Amino acid sequence: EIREIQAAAAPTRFARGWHCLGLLRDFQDGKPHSIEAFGTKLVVFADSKGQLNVLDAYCRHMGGDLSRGEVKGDSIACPFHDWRWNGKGKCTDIPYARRVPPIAKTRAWTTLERNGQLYVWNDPQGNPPPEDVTIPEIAGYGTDEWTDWSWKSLRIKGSHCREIVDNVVDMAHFFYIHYSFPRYFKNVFEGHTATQYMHSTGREDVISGTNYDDPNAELRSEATYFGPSYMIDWLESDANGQTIETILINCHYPVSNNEFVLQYGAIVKKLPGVSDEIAAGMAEQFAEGVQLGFEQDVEIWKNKAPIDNPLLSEEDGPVYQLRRWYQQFYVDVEDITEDMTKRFEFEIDTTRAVASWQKEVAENLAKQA
Amino acid sequence: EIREIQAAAAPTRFARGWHCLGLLRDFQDGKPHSIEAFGTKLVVFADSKGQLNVLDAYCRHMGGDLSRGEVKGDSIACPFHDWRWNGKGKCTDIPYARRVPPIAKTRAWTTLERNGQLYVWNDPQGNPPPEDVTIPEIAGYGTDEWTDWSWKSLRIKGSHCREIVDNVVDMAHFFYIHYSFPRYFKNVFEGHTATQYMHSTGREDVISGTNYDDPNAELRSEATYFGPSYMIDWLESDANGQTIETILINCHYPVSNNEFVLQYGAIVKKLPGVSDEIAAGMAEQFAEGVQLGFEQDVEIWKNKAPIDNPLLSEEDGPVYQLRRWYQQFYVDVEDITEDMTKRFEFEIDTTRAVASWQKEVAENLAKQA
Amino acid sequence: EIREIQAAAAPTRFARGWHCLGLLRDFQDGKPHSIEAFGTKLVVFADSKGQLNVLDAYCRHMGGDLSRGEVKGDSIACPFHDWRWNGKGKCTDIPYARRVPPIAKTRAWTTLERNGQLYVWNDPQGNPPPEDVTIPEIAGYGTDEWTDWSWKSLRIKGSHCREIVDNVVDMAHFFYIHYSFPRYFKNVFEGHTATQYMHSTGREDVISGTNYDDPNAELRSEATYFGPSYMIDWLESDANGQTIETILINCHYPVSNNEFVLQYGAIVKKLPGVSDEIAAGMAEQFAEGVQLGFEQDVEIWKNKAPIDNPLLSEEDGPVYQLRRWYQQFYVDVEDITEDMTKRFEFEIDTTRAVASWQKEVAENLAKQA
Ligand SMILES: C[C@]12CCC(=O)C=C1CC[C@@H]1[C@@H]2CC[C@]2(C)C(=O)CC[C@@H]12
Ligand SMILES: C[C@]12CCC(=O)C=C1CC[C@@H]1[C@@H]2CC[C@]2(C)C(=O)CC[C@@H]12
Ligand SMILES: C[C@]12CCC(=O)C=C1CC[C@@H]1[C@@H]2CC[C@]2(C)C(=O)CC[C@@H]12
Ligand code: FES
Ligand code: FES
Ligand code: FES
Ligand SMILES: [Fe+3]
Ligand SMILES: [Fe+3]
Ligand SMILES: [Fe+3]
């Protein structure tokens, strides 16, 4: 009769897939950069041609942190004894010795530079990514007609990253936590992707930058995880008689199985006749509206319990199917089963919820008399 | 020849019994309140009639912290998706859905409202409290002739709560740590209670509010634990020719097996002809004198080792019998043995100690010339 | 092909040997002093004749921290109930009782007062130190012709103390981390000692107090660990036509197997015709130059990985032989093998490294045009 919460320990294994480490522009300063991810530490640095390299951060000589070193030429120089390591992981020079042991080779991670971002491939099995597991090129990025990224990040301590992934099915929380108003909500999972289609409006009683200065903006969203960690969200807003195109990133990487970094950011297509500056300000506003919602999630996650047996209502999204899909990335590729990857679609009938949320928004308006 | 300290790991099991969570007045503000106890988290809230309810804090939908929610009607509303939970643990409404799953029932803890306090019943076996395991009604509380509580609390990190319980037999430390002067000291353990009878005086060399502005006040104390965690101490002071009646609470709850909350507080009987205000100031002073002693204990506990094999002198209280009594609350009721619960009495002959403490207080007086 | 880092968990066992706890002058204030070492806590205090005593800090009565007590006579008085413990570990008085249980005896550690320092003997097997395992008397210490110690300390969190010991063979890091310029480098390990002989010069491009105000000072160093934790370094500098004699301590004690205290300090022989004050200022300057290098090591250690399989170059010192020697102190004396203790000598041919470091220092000079 009393329902109890069940929760297994978070896996120690990290998701197999592409993970965005951040913006190319932040990494292309010619300095080394430290990334604590997947239970270890990595070093990111640009070579003299500007290509980004990602190595295990721990120097194979005496364990020094390469990310606290310095770039010299096309090699990263260790701060402890200045050995030089290139983008292939090869030690290219021990500056105080004649020869280099041939076995001096560390791990260079597989990278992708795309969409103004740096992605790395994680796989505990150690295989390269298949050609068909990739990150889509966002068509508009880098054209004159779109802004650069307004980009933000948040460090979440005390939660496993499944907590963020669960949101792809959580229609109700976009009302309570993101202060939007969902009207249509549909999920489709298939292969290594998970998609949410939503149509929402702003709420009258709460003001958010995501509405682009129209409290009743309709927003059409197609949001897809391409693998375990990286979502692209294509949005179109009808705000004050205009149609605005926004592309929002929602992504993360695990620091450990109890800590992750959440990065999110927006580009906006320049409306006819608006300057670069005005468009950049629309991107920034949209990103700040997203921030508000994510900071609320952070408070939810900070205080909540993990739960493997959530009790779902009739108006809930397909959490269990999402989780079964997500599990593919935590088993060897050989152990993947059809029920993880088979096409699964579910649409929530929102008519109940909309009735209720309208009453709520209305009597929160009456709340001025 | 070298004596070594032995100490088993602190139990993971929490004491079976009534635990005071705090003052009703603090909980009856219509807001939810978070309590981290017994290795979990609880939510306390008043319904619309003012009755207090205590539930598991973790929402059975998706794990949300109910204690960061809001009270609506007679239900607590989860901050994540606003499901409503009543005092019986029943989900009364999913505001955006037509129906509620019948299996939506969480744990409502058994409570007691008494003595201006809220108590909850803990039992890992999951049974209700027997009729004869209860908290005494303090006769004077809530009458015109007694004050309300002057109440204080302290959070102790890095100790198991047995450390506070041990004090019920520790005559000597009331001199060194509490700066009183014990003259008579007797213990009686029986059933689920443990009692200390003491007569003490203030020390000349040290000034304390517990002496009510008479450095030589005699104090008669009857102090009893009613179960594992909650002590009521009935005190009568003869200070400046008056007889003052005080009732002191000393209680705690375990946060984890290495952290606990200590709450203590006093009511004073109004002397003939004194105002409510004057009496409240006597309660506050008494509570501040107790605080001094407890803050010293905190320093003792912060730095000490746990010890299962204490080496006792002739003037020590019956630590081992106290601990055997205390063990009853950490075994199933079926496994309780007669030697835990049998009447056991021991009186310390204080004549040695008094001689010594007088010399000490005297030569600390001479300490002005 | 990819080389991986291997690292076993740090031992839980602590090194057998003499460990310096600090300066006698700091301990001879008549107050008790707390030392967290070897996974436990110790109390240091002077008796009424000024002799230092070291006991287990945890009182055998009820676990009180003796190091937060007070010295009375030749005994330390516990802060909880004022029992008195002498330098032999014997309880000498329970001030409020007639008798003391004969079995009231705690652990007095074996100490040495020498070189203005206090050393204690650690051995998990519980044996006394053999006559031939000792700390050398530094001839000059306490004579008119030498200063007292300029002494410094650093607390290192998140590293095992093997990290500091490894430096005895690490020629290259004296250039990159200590900003000296090694010209000759030789190790000899034998018995319970490990020695580094080095000749170095200052670097032009970097200024350090260790050069005594001559940027090209030659320095001759004989540095020896006498057991696992304590190194004496005899130095002679030829700076601005003078010959300066310095003796530098480099030592530590383990707090836990992941935290240690590093203490280091210098005495200087008074040059003909210089005052005590001028000599003390040379000691202080030398100590501050050492500090600079050690603070850099702290940054190296803070960020590095532990590594049991370091990959060594032709110009590396004999790390593996050093570690095998060091292992003697973590096995029972009976289990020591000849390969740990046999004489082993290795000299690095520095000619390669010197060429390279000169180029580097030179083009860092050109770095002003
Ligand atoms: C990116 C996102 C979060 C996590 C997730 O899993 C799916 C989505 C898609 C909808 C986005 C939302 C973030 C907040 C957005 C911008 C709104 O305020 C309305 C639409 C909504
Ligand atoms: C409440 C208490 C503490 C813990 C315990 O176990 C038993 C007692 C009873 C005596 C109280 C004492 C607290 C300090 C008091 C008020 C004094 O200063 C003299 C009498 C003494
Ligand atoms: C004490 C020490 C550190 C750890 C070790 O293992 C061996 C030595 C001996 C050489 C000392 C060095 C400390 C820094 C010194 C003073 C210099 O700047 C040049 C010589 C060098
Ligand atoms: S640890 Fe990297 S060069 Fe030595
Ligand atoms: S987690 Fe409580 S309503 Fe969803
Ligand atoms: S604990 Fe040291 S005297 Fe009681
Ligand atoms: Fe969210
Ligand atoms: Fe106490
Ligand atoms: Fe060093």
Image: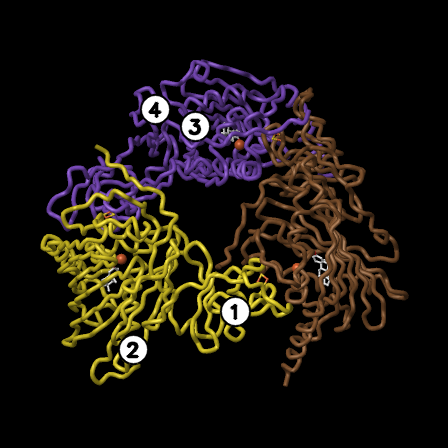
Chain colours: A purple, B brown, C yellow
Q: Which residue is mark 4?
A: A134
Q: Residue at x 74, y 67 (%)?
A: B183
Q: Are marks 1 and 2 in contact (CB under 8 Å)?
A: no
Q: Identify the image quadrant of the N terminus of chain C.
A: top left
The front one of B215 and C107 is C107
Asked if labels 2 and 4 share a chain, the reply is no
Q: Which residue is mark 1?
A: C76
- Amino acid at dot 2: Thr
For the residues marked 2 and 4, what is the alpha-carbon distance in whole angstroms?
A: 69 Å
Q: Residue at x 41, y 72 (%)?
A: C26
Q: Is C170 positioned to the left or the right of B230 in the image?
A: left
Q: Ligand 1 within 8 A of label 3's CB? A: yes
Dot 1 or dot 2: first in sequence order is: 1
Q: Which residue is mark 3?
A: A231
For the residues marked 2 and 3, what is the alpha-carbon distance in whole angstroms?
A: 68 Å
Asked if labels 3 and 4 share a chain, the reply is yes
- Amino acid at dot 4: Thr
**Residue found farthest to the right:** B273
Asked if labels 1 and 3 share a chain, the reply is no
- Amino acid at dot 3: Met
The front one of A225 and C267 is C267
